[PDB]
Amino acid sequence: MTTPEIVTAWAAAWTGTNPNALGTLFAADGTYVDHAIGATMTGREQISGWKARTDAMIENVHVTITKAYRAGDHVTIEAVYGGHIKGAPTPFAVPMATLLRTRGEEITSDQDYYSLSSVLAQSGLPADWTP
Amino acid sequence: TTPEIVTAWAAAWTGTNPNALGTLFAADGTYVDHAIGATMTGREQISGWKARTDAMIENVHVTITKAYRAGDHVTIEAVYGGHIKGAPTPFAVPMATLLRTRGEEITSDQDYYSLSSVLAQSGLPADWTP
Ligand SMILES: [Cl-]
Ligand SMILES: [Cl-]
Ligand SMILES: [Cl-]
Ligand SMILES: [Cl-]
Ligand SMILES: [Cl-]
Ligand SMILES: [Cl-]
Ligand SMILES: [Cl-]
């Protein structure tokens, strides 16, 4: 029912145009893993850099919260991730599952899962497409 | 502490009995595999998804890394492994499974994992389909 503020902040950081708004949420040794793409970042500079890299490749990145729920230091997010890969025929929107581990307000771990096949198919890109 | 429903779900996926998976679900329960894009509703179809998976993949096994419950919601961090029949090599990948429960029954299961990692580990092309 009630969405944790950290979830709202995470979505706003991904939907905005400010890489540091994402990185600042993370611990100094915090990790970020995108399992769909297979990218791994550690620390705020690299994590803010992942928002920057994503924006460089994808226009109009936006993340909306479907629902979220906390169990102790763990937060689960069901979201929709959308955008338009620059140069691709069409945009995409897919469900995503994000698992956070937190310490107070700080994020120590973020894992993102979503269907890369669905992203590419919606986008009109080949199934084996790479940037 | 891992919920018993999580242990049961892993044992169903790791075993050789399709009905052990389906019996865990409500009559109108849903199962979505986002990596492959498959949707099933009801125990017969859900059991059938275990059968279909086993027909395509040898030694399917699911191990629990950690799991947690928030109300009627359970999150599972697991490792999903097996060997796609005919592929050069086996695979093992992390998976995130989101359950919605009612008592012991599962009303919704969503599975997420990297299909690109599955295929790459397996020695299959990136645009490989059955
Ligand atoms: Cl909730
Ligand atoms: Cl909810
Ligand atoms: Cl994924
Ligand atoms: Cl834990
Ligand atoms: Cl826990
Ligand atoms: Cl997925
Ligand atoms: Cl995927």
Image: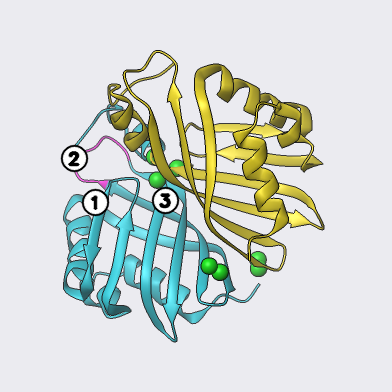
Chain colours: A cyan, B yellow
Say which residue label 3 marks: A113
Residue drawn at point x = 29 percent, y = 67 percent: A31
Q: Residues within 10 Å of mark 3 (few under 14, many from 20)?
A: many
Q: Is residue A36 above or below residue B22?
A: below
> Can see residue A85?
yes
User: Which of the two residues, A8 or B33, is positioned nearer the viewer here?
Assistant: B33
Instruction: Locate residue A52, reporting x and y percent.
Output: 18, 63
Magenta-colored stretch includes residue A86: yes
Instruction: Locate residue A47, reporting x and y percent.
Output: 23, 68
Foreground tag (1 vs 2):
1
Q: Is mark 1 within 8 Å of ligand 7?
A: no
Residue A87: numbered disc: 2
Magenta-highlighted stretch: main secondary structure? loop
Residue drawn at point x = 33 percent, y = 26 percent: B122
Say which residue label 1 marks: A58
Instruction: Left or right? Give the position of A70 relative to A84.
Output: right
Compare marks 3 and 2 and give the one earlier in the sequence. Answer: 2
Instruction: Left or right? Give the position of A71 relative to B103.
Output: left
Q: CA distance from mark 3 to mark 2?
A: 24 Å
Instruction: Locate residue B8, reporting x and y percent.
Output: 70, 46
> Can see residue A115?
no
Q: CA distance from mark 1 to mark 2?
A: 9 Å
SS category of the residue bearing label 3: strand
Q: CA distance from mark 3 to mark 1?
A: 17 Å
